[PDB]
Image (tube, rainbow, N blue to C red; front, side, top):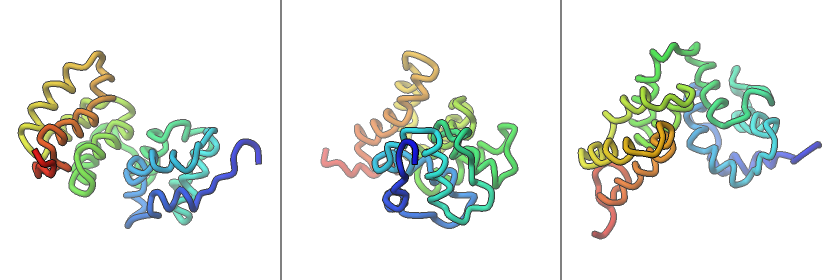
Length: 180
């Protein structure tokens, strides 16, 4: 094969194979995508796409093509888009609602902006409402807002998210796991 043969099962091991529904798999990916990227260098667009579909194996129509999956964000979004008939930014509210509940605000934010196509702010607005501790909400709203660009806010949102999870020292939900 030209490029790199997909270890796939290695990747699936990273993701931990499909979760419950197909409809979950999109968002599910955006979580696992970086992890997949660990196994798989996914040095081509081709690769990226073949991984996803190969993960899920029997996914209805999420089976993207080696030309849509150039980024993980586009693919993950599209698989969800597959199952939810696509959205006119109507759905992102609900999309955020589901992941945050399941995985947490940081991840949901991530899918939401991917699903939304890098207009984080809308997804973020819903997300914001999903923060664990008001310190997190406030602080995030403060620093992540203040970023160097609009998308810098997009980029570092989760980092600040995790950051506030750091300073409050949570895993997320205002736990304060960290010693201090």
